[PDB]
Image (cartoon, rainbow, N blue to C red):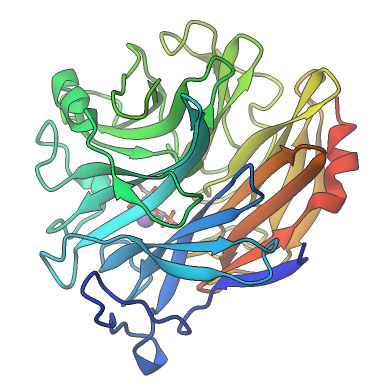
Length: 381
Ligand SMILES: CC(=O)N[C@H]1[C@H]([C@H](O)[C@H](O)CO)O[C@H](P(=O)(O)O)C[C@@H]1O
Ligand SMILES: [K+]
């Protein structure tokens, strides 16, 4: 496919609202100022769908944001863009939908793309600051789906708000960021992050929600330690294993009882160092013969700060516990205003295998085809 391309250009995109009016951002010429938090999902048709926060006015988290979607049917050479999910537009300074997590799955025979984003309107502080209510009244977690290969998206009426309210100890919940997965048994699984109510000692926890149809969701009874909460889950034999953001070394836990109890997973626990503050990272599995190998992307953060330099691809040997840097695909110092995030996507359509990444590059979202690295990754078992 193309080796590298720009999916969304900082200060170079113009979006229209649901009425057809142009959204005037703070970028030059009234363009969208900054893009963050990329999520990518590839379909059985080879279609690449990329989601990202379109932070129209500033890179700040508490700002005016819509979820943009870019679709490529030519291997990432050209992109068709639009807004997939619009914020409520209650507050022109703060209304937002943010931090996408997507899943491409076959739900009862229908290939579907799901995108889940957190939604806020009047909260002006970071989401972790709201722990008085269960749940926070300004918050919501919305799910949209596409059943036509990423062309149109529509809201799914879900029971997610209900399960959170019923739990009673969760102030807000968000996807783990990047991509979720469909288990071997067909269940849809979104890794999640959660801010607990003020009474709970642990402020953050990680877990997941699962569903068979994408409409009715469930939360398991247990909780995994929170750390930097952003996380991805992979299926390994009869276990679900997560890979969590943490200031310093990443953490990885395993559940053998479907979310009831979690224990450290040695093969990936404390293997990659993201240094100061930590960063979101993407972790997926790639089959090789009858075995599995985990591919992972996150920043080396050579400056030990918010610049999160050197977004790299790592291979994790799930059997021996060995880790190897495969490719430092973005060996640059990022913009401290918001940098370092990424999302990997592997797919084998018939006999064609592709490994793609999407990542933050100074306010823009870039795409790279990393398929040439597959033989090396696949040998790590
Ligand atoms: C919902 C939300 O706030 N998401 C933001 C999170 C969040 O604030 C932290 O994880 C603390 O919870 O921070 C990151 P970053 O600043 O590390 O790049 C950007 C995300 O868009
Ligand atoms: K933040």
